[PDB]
Image (cartoon, coloured by chain):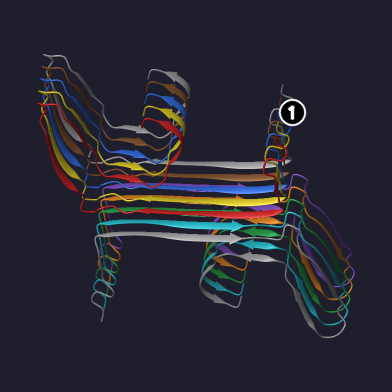
Chain colours: A green, B cyan, D orange, E purple, F red, G yellow, H blue, I brown
Amino acid sequence: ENLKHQPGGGKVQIINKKLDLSNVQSKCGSKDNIKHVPGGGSVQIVYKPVDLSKVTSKCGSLG
Amino acid sequence: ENLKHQPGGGKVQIINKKLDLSNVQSKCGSKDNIKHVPGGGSVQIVYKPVDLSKVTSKCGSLG
Amino acid sequence: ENLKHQPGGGKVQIINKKLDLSNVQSKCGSKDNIKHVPGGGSVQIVYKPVDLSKVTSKCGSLG
Amino acid sequence: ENLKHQPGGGKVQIINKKLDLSNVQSKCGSKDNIKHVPGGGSVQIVYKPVDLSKVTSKCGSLG
Amino acid sequence: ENLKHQPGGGKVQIINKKLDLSNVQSKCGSKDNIKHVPGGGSVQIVYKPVDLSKVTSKCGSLG
Amino acid sequence: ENLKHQPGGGKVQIINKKLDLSNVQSKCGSKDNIKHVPGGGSVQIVYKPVDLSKVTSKCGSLG
Amino acid sequence: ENLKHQPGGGKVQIINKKLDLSNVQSKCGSKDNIKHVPGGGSVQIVYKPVDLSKVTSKCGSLG
Amino acid sequence: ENLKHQPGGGKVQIINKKLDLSNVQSKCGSKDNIKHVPGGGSVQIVYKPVDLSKVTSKCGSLG
Amino acid sequence: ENLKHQPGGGKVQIINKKLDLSNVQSKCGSKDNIKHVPGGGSVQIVYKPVDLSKVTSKCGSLG
Amino acid sequence: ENLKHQPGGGKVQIINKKLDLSNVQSKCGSKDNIKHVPGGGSVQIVYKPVDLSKVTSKCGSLG
């Protein structure tokens, strides 16, 4: 079915991966006020500032 | 079915990947006020400032 | 079915990928006020400023 | 089925992976107030600032 | 089925992995107040600032 | 004599210097033959291919 | 004589210097033959291929 | 004579110096033949391939 | 004579110096033949391939 | 004469010096033949391949 399957014929190979990830933040910081009082039937979710530069995920189910 | 399957014939190969990711933020920071009081049947969701420079995901189900 | 399947015949190959991603932000920051009081049947969603420079996603189901 | 299965023919190979991950934070820090009083049937979740530079995950079920 | 299974023919190979992970924090620290009083049927969860530079996970079930 | 001497009044300044210097060479290389046999009173000088992309020189005497 | 001497009044300054210096060479290499036989009164000088990307020199006497 | 002498008034300053110096060589190498036989009054000098990426010299006398 | 002498007033300063020095060589190597037979009054000098990436010299006399 | 002499007023300072020095060599090695037979009045000097990545010299006399 597959004899070579993508053969790579070379002699000299030089690669330089330059990954410059610069994440700046707020020196003063953030300020938020949230109020939650269960009584009926509702959903509430609050997340704080997060830093996502790089991530490696091949396969994931329900994050 | 596949003999070579995309053959690469070369002698000298030099590649330089330059990834310049510069993410700036608000030195003063952000300010937001949210109010939530369960009683009926509604949905509420609040997220804070996030930084997404680069991400590698081959396959993902329900994020 | 496929003998070569896109053959690449060369001797010298030099490539330089220049990715200049500059994301500026508001030094003063943003300010927004949201009010939510469950009682009937409605949906509400609030997101904060996010920075999306680059993203790599081959396949994704329901984000 | 597979004879070579992606053969790599070379003589000299030099690669330099440069991963520059710079995560800045808020010297002043963040300030948020959350109120929760169980009584009805609602869901509430609060997360604090997190730093995600790099992550390696091949397979994951329910995170 | 597999004779070579991805053969690697070379003479000299030099690789230098440069992983620069810099995680900054808030010298001033964060301040948050949460209130929880069980009485009805709701769920509440609070997490403190965490630092995630790198992680190696091949397979995981329910984290 | 000088009070301000070129004052710079601003609030926000963002500059991005992009210096793309690409120097190509002759994969085949050069070939030159020179003959010199001292006997009289003459001067001879031979230089090989050089690459000059950028140079910073404030002051120089006799190069 | 000088009170301020070029004052710089600002609040936020972000600069990104991008220096991309790519110097290619001759994979085949160069070939030159030089002959020198002292007998009279002459001067001879031979230099080989050199790579000059960047140089920082404030002051120099006789190089 | 000098009161301030170039004062710098700021609040937030972020600079990222990107120095990409790529020096390629001749995998095949160079080949040169030189002949020198003292007998008269001449000067001869031969140098081999050198790589000059960057150099820092404030002051130098006779190099 | 000098009161401040270049004063620096700031609050937050983040700098990232990226020095990428890549020096390639000739896997095959170089080959040169030199002949010297003292008899008259001449000067001869031969140097081999050298690698100069970076150098720090404030002051130097006769190198 | 000097009161402050270059005062530095700040609160938070984060610097990351990245010095990537990669020096490659010739796996095959070099080959050179030199002949010297004193008889007259000449000077001869031969040096072998050297690697100079970085050097720190404030002051030097006759190197």
Please tell me which residue lies in front, D26 or G38: G38
Please tell me which residue lies in front, B8 or G35: G35
In the image, taking residue H53 as reference, residue G38 lies left or right, namely left
Residue assigned mark 1: I3
Circle 1 packing at 10 Å, graded few (<14), some (14-19), many (20+), is: some
Residue H17 percent coordinates (x, y): 54, 47
Q: Is residue G46 in view?
A: yes
Q: Is residue A32 placed above or below I30 in the rendered structure?
A: below
Please tell me which residue lies in front, F1 or G24: F1
Residue type, mark 1 in image: Leu
Q: Residue at x 28, y 66 (%)?
A: E2
Residue I11 percent coordinates (x, y): 73, 44
Residue H26 percent coordinates (x, y): 26, 47
Helix, strand or loop at label 1? It is loop
Q: Residue at x 15, y 17 (%)?
A: I41
Q: Is residue E62 in view?
A: no
- Quarter of the image with the N terminus of chain G in it: top right
Residue G44 percent coordinates (x, y): 19, 30
The quadrant in which residue F7 appears is top right
Chain ID for label 1?
Answer: I
- Quarter of the image with the C terminus of chain G in it: top left
Residue farthest to the front, as pictured? F1
Count of labels shown? 1
In the image, taking residue H11 as reference, residue B55 lies left or right, namely left
In the image, taking residue B41 as reference, residue G17 lies left or right, namely left
